[PDB]
Amino acid sequence: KHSISDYTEAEFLQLVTTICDAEATSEEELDKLITHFEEMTEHPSGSDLIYWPKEGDDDSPSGIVNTVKQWRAANGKSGFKQ
């Protein structure tokens, strides 16, 4: 559970799908999925990507996983397992 490279896309999407469902996490659980998410993604927007998106950014789970997938490949950092 160490870097995004230990995620499959399908897996990391489930992570992002849980994050974006209030109802699905207690707050102490959320705190830690959100910290995780930032750490995996090493995106400089951290949780902004999820809660404070630029207008016309696709802020659905798959859309957050997309912009992540893309930023990372664009920056020659590693991608998912598979």
Image (spheres, rainbow, N blue to C red):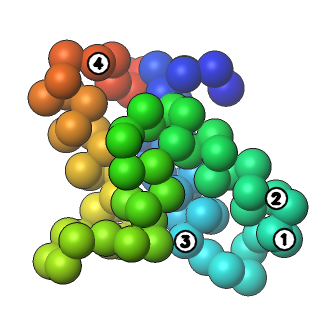
CB atoms at circles 3 and 1 under 8 Å apart? no
Neighbours of disc 2 within 10 Å: few (<14), some (14-19), many (20+): few
- The residue positioned 73% from the left and 82% from the top of the image is 23
Label 4 is placed on what type of residue? Lys
| 52 in relation to 68, above or below | below
Horizontal side, residue 12 vs residue 70: left or right:
right
Q: Quadrant of residue 6?
A: top right
* Residue pointed to by mark 1: 26
For the question of whether residue 76 can be seen, the reply is yes
CB atoms at circles 1 and 2 under 8 Å apart? yes
Dot 1 lies on which element? loop
| 48 in relation to 45, above or below | below
Quarter of the image with the N terminus in it: top right
CB atoms at circles 4 and 2 under 8 Å apart? no
Dot 3 lies on which element? loop
Dot 4 lies on which element? loop
* Residue pointed to by mark 4: 77
Neighbours of disc 1 within 10 Å: few (<14), some (14-19), many (20+): few
Horizontal side, residue 54 vs residue 33: left or right:
left
Between the residue at mark 3 and the residue at mark 1, the CA separation in whole angstroms equals: 12 Å
- The residue positioned 37% from the left and 40% from the top of the image is 43
Q: Nearer the viewer, residue 38 or 3?
A: 38
Q: Of the residues under marks 3 and 1, which one precedes in the sequence? A: 3
Q: Residue 53 at what x, y percent from top left? A: 31, 70
* Residue pointed to by mark 2: 29
Quarter of the image with the C terminus in it: top left
Label 2 is placed on what type of residue? Glu
Label 1 is placed on what type of residue? Ser
Q: Residue 16 at what x, y percent from top left? A: 52, 57
Dot 2 lies on which element? helix
